[PDB]
């Protein structure tokens, strides 16, 4: 029979374009392998999580129990992912996290069957704060949504930014997924920082970018790369000049990215973004696992071990996991110019996030 891959992703709401991009990355990878991973035909069972933490336990349980998923892949929203990972850890099902950066997933909640192909919130926030200090910035206002990802990315940023003698003047938070920003933009203007660090993504990011430009603040906008990835063409000139830090840049010239961009543009007529890459690499990681156990997904201990030691070429560069199952990869400084984020160079060389509390 087919190998059933349960996909828990947002197909509606503000993160719907992220779930679409991840799904596209996975399906394109499965197609590049002739519809099979390690000799098994793939069947995706797609469930919309609606980025809604109150539904996460029920929808995960259904995917594992009622639909009998052989593998679980998800999700985008860190609150949903934390609840999902709690159920997956206790079940033992091979689980791949293709976006959610919740720090706990590769720290205190680290597990033998739980892998991440994206990043950790805290680590990318620290890399962005470091880049802003190197750029001479000293007085920030942060703006994000009131949930674990905003908090952890703003916390990581504040750690590096204050360690660099900068001050964080205010942390503005908006309830998730609200996108009424006029009040935050009036407060930014009143506080006169020399920079703004924002975490938004999907619909929220695109609207924040247009609203932020329409305010004519004269203040540079920064953030983790999720603030611009995927929304460059739609943001138009309002995006110009935004500086971000991310573990992917569309112009990386390694052969795997050039072939991946080609396949993705030929199938979907738009460039891939970081979300598509993370999905493509979840496909590569599951392939490495199913190949090592000759299609026999029931050998979980051996499947997990192979995915932990997996080594392949990502569109990002060499893919490799730490002992706590998080990617070890470079972070680049970028600028949004003319509809794409361009590479301004290396921001942080590849190092393993510190796995505080990980029993592994």
Image: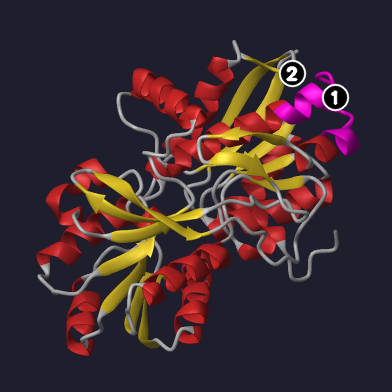
Q: Residue at x 87, y 28 (%)?
A: 298
Residue, x 12% and y 70% (percent of image)? 215
Question: Can residue 174 be seen?
Answer: no
Q: Quadrant of the N terminus?
A: top right
Instruction: Depth check: give the residue in front, 215 or 355.
Output: 355
**Residue at the extreme top of the image, as rendered:** 34
Q: Is residue 295 magenta?
A: yes
Q: Quadrant of the C terminus?
A: bottom right
SS of the residue under disc 2: loop
| 182 w.r.t. 104: above or below | below
Q: For residue 107, what is the image quadrant?
A: bottom right
Mark nearer the N terminus (2 vs 1): 2
Helix, strand or loop status at disc 1 = loop
Residue 204 located left or right of residue 162: left
Density class for disc 1 (Cα within 10 Å; few <14, some 14-19, many ≥20) is: some
Please state the horizontal and vertical placement of residue 78, each as a whole percent of the image. 56, 58
Instruction: Name the residue located 54 percent from the left edge and 36 percent from the top edge.
Output: 279
Can you identify the residue that label 2 sits on?
A: 38
Magenta highlight range: 288-303
Residue linked to disc 1: 293
């Amino acid at each position: 029979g087919a190998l059933k891959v349960g996909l828990l992703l947002p197909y509606s709401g503000t993160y719907a374009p992220l779930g679409e991009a991840i799904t596209r990355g996975l399906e394109l990878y499965v197609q590049s392998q002739g519809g099979k991973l390690g000799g098994r035909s793939i069947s995706f069972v797609k469930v919309d999580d609606e980025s809604a933490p109150p539904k996460a336990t029920e929808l995960t349980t259904k995917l594992i129990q009622s639909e009998k998923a052989d593998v679980l892949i998800g999700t985008v929203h860190s609150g949903v992912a934390m609840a999902m990972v709690k159920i997956a850890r206790e079940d033992g099902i091979p689980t791949i996290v293709p976006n959610a950066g919740a720090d706990i997933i590769t720290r205190a909640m680290c597990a033998p069957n739980v892998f991440r192909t994206s990043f950790a919130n805290g680590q990318i926030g620290r890399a962005t704060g470091d880049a802003m200090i190197k750029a001479g910035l000293k007085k920030a206002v942060t703006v994000t949504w009131k949930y674990a990802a905003g908090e952890e990315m703003v916390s990581g940023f504040k750690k590096s930014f204050t360690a660099g003698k900068g001050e964080v003047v205010k942390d503005i938070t908006i309830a998730f997924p609200d996108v009424e920003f006029q009040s935050a933009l009036a407060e930014i203007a009143s506080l006169k920082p020399d920079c703004v660090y924002a975490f938004f993504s999907g619909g929220g990011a695109l609207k924040f970018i247009k609203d932020y430009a329409a305010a004519n603040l004269g203040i540079p906008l920064w953030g983790p790369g999720f603030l611009t990835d995927g929304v460059e063409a739609a943001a138009g000139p309002a995006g110009d000049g935004i500086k971000t830090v991310l573990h992917y840049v569309s112009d990386l010239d390694n052969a795997e990215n050039q072939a991946f961009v080609k396949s993705f543009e030929a199938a979907y007529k738009i460039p891939p973004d970081v979300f598509a890459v993370q999905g493509w690499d979840a496909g590569q990681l599951l392939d490495a696992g199913v190949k090592a156990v000759g299609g026999d997904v029931a050998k979980r201990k051996e499947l997990n071990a192979a995915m932990a030691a997996a080594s392949f070429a990502s569109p990002r560069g060499p893919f490799k996991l730490s002992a706590a199952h998080n990617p070890v990869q470079n972070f680049y400084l970028r600028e949004l110019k003319g509809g794409k984020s361009v590479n301004l160079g290396l921001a942080a060389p590849a190092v393993a996030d510190e796995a505080i509390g990980c029993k592994l």
